[PDB]
Image (tube, coloured by chain):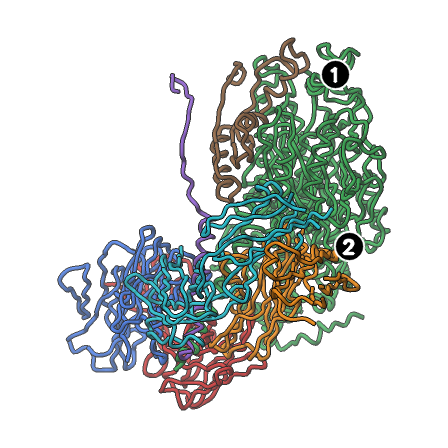
Chain colours: A green, B brown, C purple, D red, E cyan, F orange, G blue
Amino acid sequence: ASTDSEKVAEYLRRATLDLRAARQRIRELEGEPVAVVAMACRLPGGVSTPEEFWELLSEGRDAVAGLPTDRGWDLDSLFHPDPTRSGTAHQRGGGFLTEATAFDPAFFGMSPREALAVDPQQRLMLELSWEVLERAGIPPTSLQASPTGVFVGLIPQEYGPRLAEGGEGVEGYLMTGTTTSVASGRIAYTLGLEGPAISVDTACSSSLVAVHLACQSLRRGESSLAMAGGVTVMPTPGMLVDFSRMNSLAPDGRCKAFSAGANGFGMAEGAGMLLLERLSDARRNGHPVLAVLRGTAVNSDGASNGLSAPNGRAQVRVIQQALAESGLGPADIDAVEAHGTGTRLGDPIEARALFEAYGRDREQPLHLGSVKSNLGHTQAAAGVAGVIKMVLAMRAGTLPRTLHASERSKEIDWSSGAISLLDEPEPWPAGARPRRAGVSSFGISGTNAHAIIEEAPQVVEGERVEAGDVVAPWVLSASSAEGLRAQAARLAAHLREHPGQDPRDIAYSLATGRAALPHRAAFAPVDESAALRVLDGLATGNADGAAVGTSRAQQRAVFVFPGQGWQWAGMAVDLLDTSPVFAAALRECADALEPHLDFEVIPFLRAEAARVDVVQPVMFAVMVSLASMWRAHGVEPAAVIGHSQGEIAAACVAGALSLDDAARVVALRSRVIATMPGVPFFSTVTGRWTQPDELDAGYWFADAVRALAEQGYRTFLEVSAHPILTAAIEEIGDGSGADLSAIHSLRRGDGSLADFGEALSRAFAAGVAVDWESVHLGTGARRVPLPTYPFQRERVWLEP
Amino acid sequence: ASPTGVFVGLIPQEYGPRLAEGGEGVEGYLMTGTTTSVASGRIAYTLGLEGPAISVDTACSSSLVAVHLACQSLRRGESSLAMAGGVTVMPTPGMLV
Amino acid sequence: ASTDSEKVAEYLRRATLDLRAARQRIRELEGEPVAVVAMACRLPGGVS
Amino acid sequence: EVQLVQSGGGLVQPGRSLRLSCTASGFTFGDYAMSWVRQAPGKGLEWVGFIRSKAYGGTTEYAASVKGRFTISRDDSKSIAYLQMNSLKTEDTAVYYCTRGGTLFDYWGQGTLVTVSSASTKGPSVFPLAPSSAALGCLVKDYFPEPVTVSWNSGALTSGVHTFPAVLQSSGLYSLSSVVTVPSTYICNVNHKPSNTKVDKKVEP
Amino acid sequence: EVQLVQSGGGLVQPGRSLRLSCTASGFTFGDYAMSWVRQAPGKGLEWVGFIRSKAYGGTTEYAASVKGRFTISRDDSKSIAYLQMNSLKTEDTAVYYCTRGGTLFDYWGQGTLVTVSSASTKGPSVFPLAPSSAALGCLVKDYFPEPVTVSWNSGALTSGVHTFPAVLQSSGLYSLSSVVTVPSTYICNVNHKPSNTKVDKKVEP
Amino acid sequence: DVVMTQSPLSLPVTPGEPASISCRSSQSLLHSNGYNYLDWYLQKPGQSPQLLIYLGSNRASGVPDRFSGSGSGTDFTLKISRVEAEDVGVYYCMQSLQTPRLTFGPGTKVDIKRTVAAPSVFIFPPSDEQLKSGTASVVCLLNNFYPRGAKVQWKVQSGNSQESVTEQDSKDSTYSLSSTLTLSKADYEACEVTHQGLSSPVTKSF
Amino acid sequence: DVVMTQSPLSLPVTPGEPASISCRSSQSLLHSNGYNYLDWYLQKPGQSPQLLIYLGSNRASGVPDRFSGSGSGTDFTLKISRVEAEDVGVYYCMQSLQTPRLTFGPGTKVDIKRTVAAPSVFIFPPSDEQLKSGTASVVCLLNNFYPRGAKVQWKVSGNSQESVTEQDSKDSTYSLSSTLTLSKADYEKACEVTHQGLSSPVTKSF
């Protein structure tokens, strides 16, 4: 059968499937686009966050004021009005950072001496990395022993005294403090990553080159996350006074790109960092996507008329190569972020190259701009700044303005009109055609780089709306008291600025996200007004209505099963019906207990809200249900010292007898005790560490807690509607060793879930690990941007 | 004008006088003659090569890592030839102190 | 023509050739060996 | 993807019918004529029967033995394949796999159990054996259902455990054996969930 | 790689025979089927002949108008295909292609041009009257065979000169055309190899 | 069992924008096994044809990735995305249901899109020279006209003639044409241009 | 008929150096079209079967490389260049000339190569234990007899039940048990065990 009809069809189908899979793999290996998750920046002026950068760009403002008077510069003989005297600069102004002199060595594991030895560049890079990691939404403490690449772009320069002469207290740390490799080695060591760490020095085009490398390791597959950035800062006026010898610096210090009055390029300083991930991986895990990088190209200009002389053919070739790698055409680009350094000779060459590379096949004019007009030349910090500007403009749907462009140059020809200089803001709305942009960077060494950036896919739309009645806790942590106070003040301020936010979104973002730190605060407000009230109360200093407490290197909790003493319970049908964990575990144990003890689950767990024969089995049942829900809520137990019925409860929890079997044995105990009236576990009646198997039929306060504390467990948690013997334990807390805290579960008739919210808030208040995804799970809460960590900086300088 | 890359491992070192008080004959060439960025650029400038010419610093392994880069550029197809290497020279007795 | 093994055979052969070429391209793009042509050195002890 | 996810099974007395369903998904079910294969416990895989595609006629073929009691359905609307039982015997106890092709056996399913017998839920009997004269052990006597676990002094001993797969006797009741070795006291425990007659027994000459 | 270089040529008067050879290398010849197609100048392609493989043996299917005058053979020692034909006719002028595959025309080979009909080399005196008073065309009426070139004032003037293809007059004598396109000193004489005429003139009114 | 290639046989195209050619049929080309018997061939000017797509949509090895195809029961369409200037040629769509095959068919050719650029006229009669042996060419020399359509006639009412045209004028790309006429020697005692871009034919005596 | 395909039975392997399995035939499997109708299947311990190679030499997508098929139409071979620890199980040859394929055949087996070791024996008498009423049972047992393959007979035979463990994992030695049953007629007076690693047969009674 199947003669020549079915036999070959199956093989043909299999071969076609294999060919399709192989070609798909080829395409993925060659041209997989990458996605930008988050960005971080530090620019001259008051700019410290990308929002301020976009606000400055939209309002059209420059950030050039003068020179710094903090870094011990002479400032005086720096310009004898004769240009050619030794030690005479030419720039009477510029754009410089005002925060480089300050640092916070306490937050990191850094000693004041070696902190004084640390270069400002890596000093800024550490903060940039931490801020971008928090902005992405990934807890910075989760990235441990994982493949994550770091790529940095710097220029060595100099900071302090020479190594030969040494210092008085800081001698051994001089070498590591000033070295380009340590700039990324320190980041890798602090964050505990394991991917490649690379520092690249390729002049003003360094930063872009870095991201190019970050776009390759991700594509090949040697790393699953990349952090690429650049930095430039000046602790010495040497660069200006040496560049003035070439007479290439404009006096005032501005960039008049494509203007009739070009005089120089000026200098500045800054820092930028981006986080990159494969698009499929990022979308699989739900990480945010801001823009997509598709193709990059790096080239050299070859032999020219000197090292500083630029080339046009190389730029054209690199642009065409980037376009070919991206697999697009010259007509798919709407705007370009040209270099626009503002020099006399560079501008015509770059303009001609861009013309010949883009505008020959163009129906619509191409917009051109340069960020160096607003901020000046930032050396290696540039390149990434252009990328940030382009992505911000594309997201906001507006093209910003370029300054000092009202007087177009006279050495270039614009007869074709294919390139229109950006002098006024231009709307950039969404449409059928996706938006794309290109960024160029050229270095004085002779290396050129080009990149193409595209908008994120418009698939986020389609979110639904769901409501609920469960209130969720709010938590916030920091490493110092003032840090906690400032964080609370900033959160209250931001919540004041932006109204309409649901409590669920803020609760979820302040959930998994910010890391776990010594100083913690937690609460649970009904609405936002009382939330602001308690937040301002925390900001003032007196913590009332919330929970606080330091906890250094504490990660364990202890479950203790108290005996009788929580009587009258306060029947909670809401616990049984609202919580499904009860409605499963307690239901199972109850129907296990039903056949033996004639009493049903209907009669008194129906409750008349308005006898050891009955209570003890039901207290055991509700105890095991509560223990199950607690352990499912992320908090695991430890050795249990449960007394009386607590012995059977601990037997059930630690694995001595099964739920049905433990229920049956407690029913037998109740039936034999209703006549006379009228996993590591810690033994109670003997006081020893025992295995969970010896507990049998034959088996049926001070020294115990001393030994448990001496072991290393310093907290006690009892599952009871009313905490009993708490003071007895509490009095012991100061009596020996470290202090002891006991957390209640319920209150006097307060069976509402809000009581459990307070219990959880008190649990997190003192060194207890809680699985927040488990307690949130399904609520529809989505990520929401929040302010980053506020620091406490101090002056750290070392004069030469 | 041929596609050929250059990859050099380096560690920055101090050679001449400080920048803010340059000499009498060597004033405008101090920045160019000390930075590592041109440490490979000159190699591209003299021979007129047109390919990625980068400089990488990764401490004592900086040369070997450079090799790991070049092979990649060869396998992707970016360049047809590559020149990898490393060099260290100490002109002052400061490193050993 | 003859039965039906006059058109399916050629298509199967072409598919096999294309699959072999694609897999060869993948292998070459992944693990192509790199041949070293020449070396130069300058080392202590008079080695040049 | 191209998951299959079979369904059905259980235990049936001799002389009864059953339905087995194969749920094609993740691919076009139009022309992907499937087949059913059977694997007996302790032997190799032996083909049962394949159903053609509707393009070529939708006919089917069977291979002796089960020819008169086995039928195949080809519900195209839901892309479901059906195997229908008829008057099963004791020797047909095997794992059934639902394949994808007719000549080239592509992606396979996950398999069922389907056992045919006639017995009641009889518990175990416990069978500690005589000492080496050190090879102490506890064989378990007749018990009908499959899941039965054994241990030594409630799992405190781990080394030397040599529990062996059960076999089948004439009565259809199985036997489970396990031994340990240690120079010189221990109590063997068994669990029988369908019988819930967990017991303990120690052996000492 | 795969090589399908042809070998042969043709310029004969009607009545005689001719032989064409296709050479294959770089792949096994014992499985594929070779085919012969032709392309006449000015029109599209059309199928000529096709031969099966050794698994079936021979069984050629010459298309039409070639039965009894065209033959196809294959050789396995050197793996060479042959398209020997007899009794040529006027409508047989074309360029022939040898291709691999019976139904799916895979990698082709270079073409061999053949010609028919009887003619002799004659005077290549071309045409005067350049666009003076691009006037009527630098025509080469009454010339044979096809290979011929054109020139303009010792190849100094190039702009606006376009060389046009053949005309295929009612009989074997041929011609092509060229112009100057200077309407706001020029007369065209060409070089003919078989007739050995190398002339370039300049007179024009 | 007749297959025809729709869409304009000229089909002007420019670099950068995508192009599509759809080939129509008369019956369903879906075999019982589940495959479409359709193939695509490309003939560049001056070289042998090459295979592009086989079995509906399957790009052969060596073909640039920008080519693609879509199929159905009776409708098939070849599509490109970033056409270059080196893709000019002739395109053929083939069925494979019936093994006995014939001439490939008219096919579809492509060229670079341009403007209209109505042609020019250079009619004048012969007097002397090689024309003295007896013949007359009425070639008006339609010069530099992009649309391909151009018919000619004569009064000084028609008969046999010959046609001769060149390639797409290299850089100019304006399809110069010199449709000429052959006349006998002793029978003594002009063109009628009908180009799309014109409005009235012109004709000069003799 | 059939070609009665066969393979060289069991073959222990070791991580590192390669391995291979041959596959013979009686009638050539080379079809007239120029292809071989053979394929290979792999069954993992306690898992569904899998497909590795089809049509003589072709690797299916998803196969973790390292597998290569080859051979003419009579002497096929499947070779693994690198031997890991997870690619252990049962391997089956398969043909396609005959459509009514009834069984997959015996199939070869692989395991971890280990130095030859000798077993131990512990005869256990049918004591007065839970046997009690009319019945009998006797087990003499085995332990650590790598490589697998042994026999047990009783004299002074015909019915017994055997059981074997699965490699014991880390130590890589089999352990086997055998049971013989009787009703009442026992106590009228020993299993003997033969393994190629050990020497002249031993035995023990009572």
Q: Position of residue A371 (x, y in %)?
A: 76, 36
The mark nearer the N terminus, 1 or 2, is: 1
Name the residue that disc number 2 marks. Answer: A430
Nearer-the-camera pick, A428 or A260: A260
Q: Position of residue A564 (x, y in %)?
A: 66, 60
Identified by mark 1, the residue type is Ala
Q: CA distance from mark 1 to mark 2?
A: 48 Å
Image height of G191 relative to A165, above or below: below
Looking at the image, can residue G135 be seen?
yes
The residue located at (32%, 75%) in the rendering is G130
The quadrant in which the N terminus of chain A is found is bottom left
Chain letter for mark 2: A
Q: Are marks 1 and 2 on the same chain?
A: yes
Left/right of residue A362 with respect to residue E167 in the rendered view: right
Identified by mark 2, the residue type is Ala
The kind of secondary structure element at disc 2 is loop
